[PDB]
Image (cartoon, grey):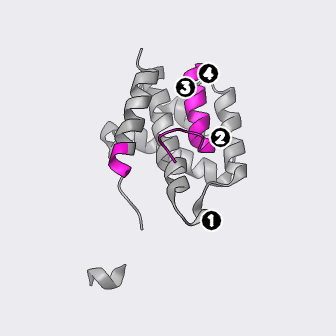
């Protein structure tokens, strides 16, 4: 039945735990609805320090938006309106205010990230990027 039953992929960032999952689901819902306020609620509800908050935010931005950008089927690509909502929200957010974090996030939402035009390499790369940026 396996071959008859059959495109979702895994998310190894789940290694962080429940808080990344919550923030990721919140970001996905808020981007699809394009009303970036649940993002604020998730960022306030979370338990971890500011730098881990920013890292989780960056990883969610990548997993949802940048991977959607990697599909050949353009209709799945993030809509300009979603870019508008998340770009504005990043601009008004403070833990993302560090020019490097804000630039990297915005580049994920706008696909202007170098290295982000393999999958496992790309995922480890973006994880290292987030950790280095946010790691003080």
Relative to 65, residue 95 above or below: above
* Nearest to viewer (mark 3 / mark 2): 3
Looking at the image, do the residues carrying marks 3 and 4 touch, with CB atoms under 8 Å apart?
yes
Q: List x then y, in percent, for residue 119.
A: 37, 51
Work out how far the residue at label 4 is from the one at label 1, CA to CA, in angstroms.
31 Å
Q: What's the distance in space between the residues labelled 4 and 2, CA to CA?
A: 14 Å
* Residue farthest to the top, as pictured: 136
* Residue 37 place in picture, x, y as percent: 65, 39
Q: Is residue 35 left or right of residue 50?
A: right
Q: In the figure, residue 19 lies in which quadrant? A: top left
Mark 2 and mark 1: span between their CA atoms?
18 Å
Residue 102 falls inside the magenta stretch:
yes
Q: Is residue 79 above or below residue 17?
A: below
CB within 8 Å, label 4 to label 1: no
Residue 36 visible, this orientation? no
- The residue that mark 4 highlights is 97
Q: Which mark is residue 86?
A: 2
Q: Is residue 1 left or right of residue 134?
A: left
Q: Residue at x 27, y 84 (%)?
A: 1
Decide: few, some or many residues near mark 4? Use Cα within 10 Å; few <14, some 14-19, many ≥20: some
Alpha carbons under labels 3 and 1: distance apart: 28 Å
* Disc number placed over residue 107 in the picture, else none: none
The residue range painted magenta reads 97-121
Distance Cα–Cα, label 3 vs label 2: 14 Å
Report the front residue among 121 and 66. 121
Mark 3, residue position: 101
Q: Which residue is mark 1?
A: 75
- N-term mark: 3 or 1: 1
Q: Secondary structure at mark 1?
A: helix
One can see residue 97 in this view: yes
């Amino acid at each position: 039945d396996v071959v008859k039953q059959q495109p979702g992929q895994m998310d190894r960032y789940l290694v962080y735990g429940d808080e990344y999952k919550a923030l990721r689901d919140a970001v996905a819902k808020a981007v699809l609805e394009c009303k970036p306020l649940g993002i604020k609620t998730a960022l306030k509800a979370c338990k971890t320090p500011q730098s881990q908050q920013s890292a989780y935010f960056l990883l969610t931005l990548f997993r949802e938006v940048a991977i959607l950008y990697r599909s050949h089927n353009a209709s799945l690509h993030p809509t300009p309106e979603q870019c508008e909502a998340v770009s504005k929200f990043i601009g008004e957010c403070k833990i993302l205010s560090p020019p490097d974090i804000s630039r990297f996030a915005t580049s994920l939402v706008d696909n202007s990230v170098p290295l982000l035009r393999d999958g496992t390499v790309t995922e480890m790369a973006i994880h290292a990027a987030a950790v280095l940026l946010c790691g003080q």
